[PDB]
Image (cartoon, coloured by chain):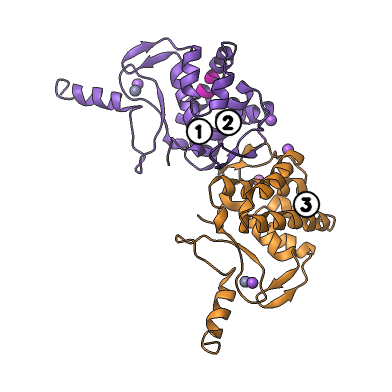
Chain colours: A purple, B orange
Amino acid sequence: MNLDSYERTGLRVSLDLVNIATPGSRRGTPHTGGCVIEDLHDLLKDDPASVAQLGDDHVEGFVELARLLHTAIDALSNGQVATAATALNHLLRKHPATPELAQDPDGTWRLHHHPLDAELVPMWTAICAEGLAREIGHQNVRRFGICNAHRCDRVYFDTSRNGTRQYCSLACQNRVKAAAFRER
Amino acid sequence: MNLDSYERTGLRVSLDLVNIATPGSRRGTPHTGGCVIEDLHDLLKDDPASVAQLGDDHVEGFVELARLLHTAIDALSNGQVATAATALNHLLRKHPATPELAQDPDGTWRLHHHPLDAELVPMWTAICAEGLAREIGHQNVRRFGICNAHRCDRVYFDTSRNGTRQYCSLACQNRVKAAAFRER
Ligand code: NA
Ligand code: NA
Ligand code: NA
Ligand code: NA
Ligand code: NI
Ligand code: NI
Ligand SMILES: [Zn+2]
Ligand SMILES: [Zn+2]
């Protein structure tokens, strides 16, 4: 899997949005969470149309989306697939999730997991929900993890062949490595 | 790609339905097309719920679906992606295409490309349309082909690594091989 591909947009944005907005800890430090519009510009950068339409009114919607996706991802990390499925199914019903083909300005045809007339927060809700749902269908639930590092509860999706990744980031991987000698 | 997998159901059923119902020629012989309910029982065998609900009233709907999918697949084989996209988008709008997670009786979670309360022909229309649409999004249009054998216009999706398959079936591959010496 290429987590940066168009095809994994919903998965990638879900992880990134939860990791921005969900309070907890990040890379060894308490993390306040929430977000500001600048976080959304960078979150949604792969879609110039979204970025062109973002306003401060979208922040509350993305914070709420983050809360819902965090609950689902945490459920998946615990094997509580039914809990995640119930929530994702409701999002797919509530928001416009009819797929639609369209051609990017460079000519590339894409399958969008929403109609092009969707509103912005409903659109991203559908995209994110389908992306997580798809990974459940693809039997990848065990690849959703919560960072094993001290004072980090950021989420990750393990893209390794072996499926034994423990840490959310190279940052946490490095922090653990750098503590190994002294903690021996 | 595994064309027999759950994940390629829409693609597989689309090809099979077109090849049953579309008049033309098949494996060297004129092909009348149409279908009967027995064709649908075998077409949809991977879904016991569909098979349990099939009736003769569904035959007309599947013949019409076949006509629409044949037009799309023939368009794809010609690189006429916009023509295919317009038709597939309309099917996805017309029919229930909201995805839904559910657990098979064996416990396996699946992403269905329709709500579980869908009617039978609308359901299969959505499944088939999404399956074809997905392959357009995955940049696989050039893998949709029309058999090169004499008096065969059956369709196929090339699953080979090299993407140079010419014939719809081992049957047509063998018929061509068996004619090579005499036609030399
Ligand atoms: Na919906
Ligand atoms: Na941790
Ligand atoms: Na629809
Ligand atoms: Na032919
Ligand atoms: Ni999109
Ligand atoms: Ni289904
Ligand atoms: Zn971490
Ligand atoms: Zn053939």
Q: Secondary structure at mark 1?
A: helix
Is ligand 5 less than 8 Å from the beta carbon at label 2? yes
Quarter of the figure with the N terminus of chain A? top left
Within the magenta stretch, is there residue A68?
A: yes
Kind of residue at disc 2? Ile
Q: Residue at x 65, y 28 (%)?
A: A90
Query: Which residue is most to the bottom?
Result: B182
- Horizontal side of A28 relative to A88 (left or right) equals left
Q: Specify the quadrant of the image occupied by residue B182.
A: bottom right
The residue mark sitting in front, 3 or 2, is: 2
Q: Specify the quadrant of the image occupied by residue A118.
A: top right
Q: Specify the quadrant of the image occupied by residue A114.
A: top right
- Horizontal side of A151 relative to A121 (left or right) equals left
Kind of residue at disc 1? Thr
Residue A127 marker:
2
Residue A9 marker:
1
Within the magenta stretch, is there residue A13?
A: no
Q: Secondary structure at mark 3?
A: helix
Q: Main secondary structure of the magenta part?
A: helix
Query: Which residue is most to the right?
Result: B57
Q: Compared to B84, does B99 lie above or below?
A: above
Kind of residue at disc 3? Gln
Residue, disc 3: B53
Q: Chain of mark 3?
A: B
| Region rendered in magenta | A66-70
**Are there few (<14), some (14-19), or many (20+) residues within 10 Å of tag 1?**
many
Q: Is residue A78 visible?
A: no
User: Of A181 and B15, which appears nearest the observer?
Assistant: B15
Q: Position of residue B150 (x, y in %)?
A: 64, 77
Circle nearer the N terminus (1, 2): 1
Do the residues under discs 1 and 2 have CB atoms within 8 angstroms? yes
Q: CA distance from mark 1 to mark 2?
A: 8 Å
